[PDB]
Image (cartoon, coloured by chain):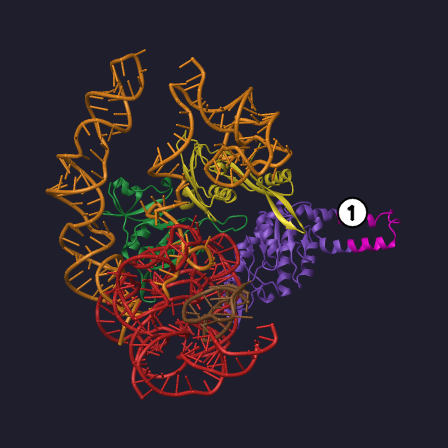
Chain colours: A green, B purple, C yellow, D orange, E red, F brown
Amino acid sequence: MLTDPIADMLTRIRNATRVYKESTDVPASRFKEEILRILAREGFIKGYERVDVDGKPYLRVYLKYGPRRQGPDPRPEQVIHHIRRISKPGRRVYVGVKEIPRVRRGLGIAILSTSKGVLTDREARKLGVGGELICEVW
Amino acid sequence: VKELLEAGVHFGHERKRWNPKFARYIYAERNGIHIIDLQKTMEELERTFRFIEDLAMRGGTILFVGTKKQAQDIVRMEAERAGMPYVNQRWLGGMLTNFKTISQRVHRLEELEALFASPEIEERPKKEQVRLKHELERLQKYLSGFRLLKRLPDAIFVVDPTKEAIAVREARKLFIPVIALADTDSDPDLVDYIIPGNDDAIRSIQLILSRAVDLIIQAR
Amino acid sequence: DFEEKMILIRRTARMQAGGRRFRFGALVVVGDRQGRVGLGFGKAPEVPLAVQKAGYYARRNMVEVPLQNGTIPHEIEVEFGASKIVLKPAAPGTGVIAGAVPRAILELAGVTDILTKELGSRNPINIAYATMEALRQLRTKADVERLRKG
RNA sequence: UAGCGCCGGCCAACUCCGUGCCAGCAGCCGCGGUAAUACGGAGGGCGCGAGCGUUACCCGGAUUCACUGGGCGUAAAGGGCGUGUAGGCGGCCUGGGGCGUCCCAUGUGAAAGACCACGGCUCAACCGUGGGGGAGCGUGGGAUACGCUCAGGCUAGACG
RNA sequence: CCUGGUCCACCCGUGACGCUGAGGCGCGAAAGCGUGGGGAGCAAACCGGAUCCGGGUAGUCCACGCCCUAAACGAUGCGCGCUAGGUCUCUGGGUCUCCUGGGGGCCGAAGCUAACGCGUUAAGCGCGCCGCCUGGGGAGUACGGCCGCAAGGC
RNA sequence: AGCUGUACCGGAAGGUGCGGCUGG
């Protein structure tokens, strides 16, 4: 069965990017909505919209790619080069304010589910709180 | 539209052959055949034609690549009615990545052509003359039209991107923009400026190439 | 304008009709110490021919490194076959910390301060290719901003 | 007062004479049967220096027990299969609790050792003064995003 | 005759009742053993010939108990989600030349692999749980323990 | 053809019976 919905979304997005689809569909959840909102704010994806697939609520994610390239293999550069799940069921990862990771010298972002909702590494450090390290994106 | 419809441009190949990557250009399916969306064809044609017009105005060089059985004569006639070179017999592997080597053959053909029109041919007895005749005939058949290229071209025009995949690869490797008259069984991603049309149906190729060459001539 | 040094010379053999035929392979890195590097592999019957061919090849397979304060913008790990390379930025006044192959590649690129590591198979050819691939996959702040925001 | 090791590759530093699978060297590869920069001596040269080498033990290189940071078609590695106990993990929509989790304040975390600053032995080792940092735990007060639990609803898993 | 699993259509009911599984329990080709029957053909060991052929006991068969191994292999643990297609074939359903499920193969996008190759039946991208590896030989050997009448197995 | 579990060799640089696999 489906054990980790968040990992499911991460893999879905990765698989969508790797084949250059304009949009993808995912089962609906509030926490997933929050994650996608964070991603959209940081300009990783073109944006999300709540839709309905044959009765069931879904979210359609519109993806963003780079410009068409030259030479052999003209496939554009990805905007999401690498997305990884940190805290998984069976081994949860919790970090304090002092242990918040820096991803790619600030070129990347990390998602923290803290007491004050879902934040990036920057804003989590700003508000001076720690939480659960959901995933890293760069 | 109204000029493309009668030429059978919008008639593709069967369901058996269609390349998935081309699906974005399919209008609908009827009678076990695929249909290309006329509208999309129209704006793609507009874009590519604008590019070709600009390149012609700047004084660029375009190479014509059509080898398919029915397209040989069309390519020949359409190319001759312009300064642009062409390849219409068979794409020798390495006309671009190995341009120098083929230029050696161009030089050889030039030297032979000069020799046969010289009053020094009274040497080299009849049999050697016949051998040289055979050599000259072969080089003329294969290397005609290509002789115009003093250097690397500025763009490439291909009738079928799949049949002439080697030429596409070479052009991609040497940063040469590609113009293709693709169909249902082609890869859109490998062509910078694509015309979704037909590769069979002499009428379609005639129309497209005639329009292209007229645009070339007009912009000079 | 471009200065040259050798990664490695090797001699390979092939059987024939009662005998051995030897061909020489050269791995050559070229650079300008300004943020541009090239790598080539040349195979020839003779050593000078191999060196010439390798340099000739390297002169086109060209890479621009986005240098800043003579160090890499960000850390990167790259897998090529069974080889792994790890590169990390360093503060000014650290020095090139690398093996023969990575040091040779990075010095010609103008890199002055970096921490490197080799993992898995340590075959020179694959390490060199991995290093080049890692160099090709480097971005700066400006590039990321342009792609994201636009 | 100037000694000790090494000079084939790893690894910095080459030439003569003696012996001819003998005497020997050897950390690995290996060197020695007429050329041997690899044995012994000499000349010369590298490295360190009142020290220089050898042996024994620990960590590293070893991502070679892989939490960071490995794997199991053919290199070592999927149990001969099923049912299932303990255990491990687990759909979405609102609430209550605040155990895990995060934050703030405070107590402790002795002295010496580690770090930083200054200072006393002619300098340094050595020592002194001062300032912090510190994993963890106790007490008091906050938050509910995620895990947990207690209530209610749903049909996309499962079952009929 | 009795009985297990499974698939499709209707979308009618329950409202998370699910996945995996150390031990345990059961099944487990062939060969082999015990208590009884049976024995046409074939055939270990064995009896003869020229140095493969002719015979021939156990065994192969049945009932009830043991034994528990293997190139027990797809040399690929189980469950769920995502990621282009083409072709052949088995079996269902529809508005029937096509559309939609569930199996068995072949070519191949992206991707993975050291390579061979795999590729919606993944050896790809992931999550959950169990089993196993730490250079070759010695060696699946020695001692100990458990199982079995024994060979032997773990 | 090779390999393999098992069961036997008083004409054993291996042989045969019952299977199984292609790593022919």
* Range covered by the magenta-colored residues: B108-135
Task: Tell me what residue is drawn at x 63 percent, y 61 percent.
Answer: B205
* Quadrant of res A108: top left
Label 1 packing within 10 angstroms: few (<14), some (14-19), many (20+) = few
Q: Looking at the image, can residue B128 be seen? A: yes
Q: Is residue D3 above or below residue B90?
A: above
Q: Position of residue A128 (x, y in %)?
A: 24, 40
SS under mark 1:
helix
Q: Amino acid at mark 1?
A: Glu
Determine which quarter of the picture holds residue E127: bottom left
User: In x, y percent, where is residue D152?
Assistant: 16, 64
B129 drawn magenta: yes
Taking the image as drawn, is residue A61 in sight? Answer: no
Of residue A103 and residue F19, the one placed in the foreground of this image is F19
The answer to whether residue D76 is left or right of residue B91 is left
Specify the subunit that label 1 lies on: B
Q: Looking at the rendering, in which quadrant would you find the N terminus of chain B?
A: bottom right
Q: Residue B130: where, in percent of width, then height? A: 83, 55
On screen, residue C59 above or below E5: above
Q: Dot 1 corresponds to which residue?
A: B111
Q: Main secondary structure of the magenta part?
A: helix
A82 or C134, nearer to the observer: C134
- Say whether residue B46 is magenta: no
Relative to A5, is D8 above or below?
above
Q: Is residue E39 left or right of residue E23?
A: right
The count of marks equals 1
Q: Nearer the viewer, residue C127 or A5?
A: C127
